[PDB]
Length: 127
Image (tube, rainbow, N blue to C red; front, side, top):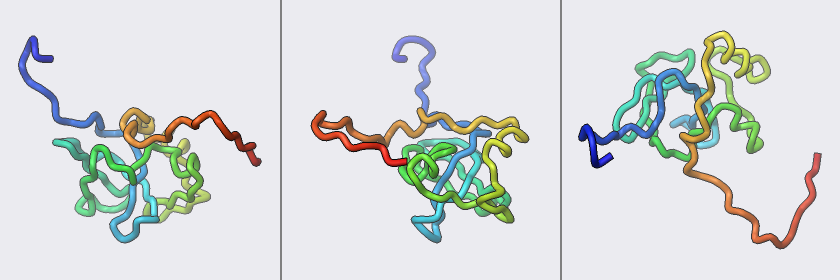
């Protein structure tokens, strides 16, 4: 705020402790789980659960590849487990209960969304 203790903010809103899903530099189709390792500027530190920190990269605070927990399933993709972990075994909730961690909020990814329908045609819901 202009009035008051001068001093604007830079951080996007991320925090240390919130889990999320990102994309691997070796493939733009593979989605791996990552955990906030640091926060600064208009970027965030992404760590590879199981891997070493040295193998950490900073992504765009407003990136599209990155998504909140339980995203892959939302859209319709298969998330890949961490180092030494299976997709069928890896259970977010299970990992979120042991580390008393809370999946990152959707407010951090409120950049990309879908536009409302023109209110014309309507398709059924297959299931």
